[PDB]
Image: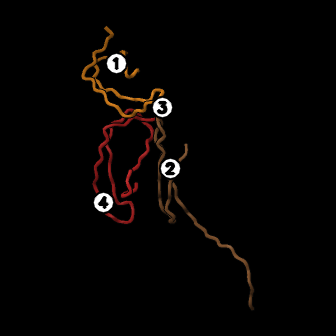
Chain colours: A brown, B red, C orange
Amino acid sequence: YEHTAVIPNQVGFPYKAHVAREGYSPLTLQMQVVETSLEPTLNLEYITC
Amino acid sequence: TDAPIISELLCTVSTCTHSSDFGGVAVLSYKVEKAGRCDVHSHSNVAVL
Amino acid sequence: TDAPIISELLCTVSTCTHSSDFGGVAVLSYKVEKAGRCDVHSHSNVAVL
């Protein structure tokens, strides 16, 4: 079974969501982020010393 | 098969603050028929469990 | 002689689907006087036990 959700980007924060399939008991997931990097791309142009 | 049946649920409250952490407590009352483990959720965006 | 006497019967419901199998559950409440084994039936053509 497939599902979609959104989570807020802030370190150390709880968020939780469902599935409610049919027949079966419900199920609750929680998602929590611990780290978030970021990285640009570079190309050198000159130096100095 | 190991899903317990729970009915006549009634919720009250005793204490709250705003504040910045888990400062609201509530009890629950329900008649059981079988032991096990159920799952909990509050379906609105104003208070997270 | 081994027929138990059962009175003040009260039926509720908790869950249903349509669907194609045994996807409706109900509990029963009754005051007993003697142990044993009784028999069950639903007297209409809209739902089979």
**Residue at (64% x, 71% y) in the render:** A39
Can you say which quadrant of the picture contains the N terminus of chain C? top left
Amino acid at pointer 4? Cys
Q: Chain of mark 3?
A: B
Which of labels 2 and 1 is toward the front? 1
Q: Secondary structure at mark 3?
A: loop
Q: Dividing the picture into quarters, in which one does residue B49 lie?
A: bottom left
Do callouts 2 and 4 mark residues in contact (Cβ within 8 Å)? no
In the rendered image of this protein, does residue A20 appear above or below residue B13? above
Q: Secondary structure at mark 2?
A: strand
Q: Chain of mark 1?
A: C
Q: Secondary structure at mark 4?
A: strand
**Residue at (33% x, 40% y) in the render:** B30
Q: Chain of mark 2?
A: A
Do callouts 1 and 4 mark residues in contact (Cβ within 8 Å)? no
Q: Can you identify the residue that label 4 sits on?
A: B16
Same chain under badges 3 and 4? The reply is yes
Q: State the mark number for residue B1.
A: 3
In the rendered image of this protein, does residue B43 appear above or below residue B22? above
Residue C17 lies, in percent from the top left, at 42, 33
Residue C8 lies, in percent from the top left, at 24, 23
Marks 1 and 4 sit apart, C-alpha to C-alpha, by 51 Å
Q: Secondary structure at mark 1?
A: loop
Amino acid at pointer 2? Leu
Amino acid at pointer 3? Thr
Q: Can you identify the residue that label 2 sits on?
A: A29
Do callouts 2 and 3 mark residues in contact (Cβ within 8 Å)? no
Which of labels 2 and 3 is toward the front? 2
Judge from the rendering whether residue A44 lies leftward or rightward of residue C18; answer left or right. right
Q: Can you identify the residue that label 1 sits on?
A: C44
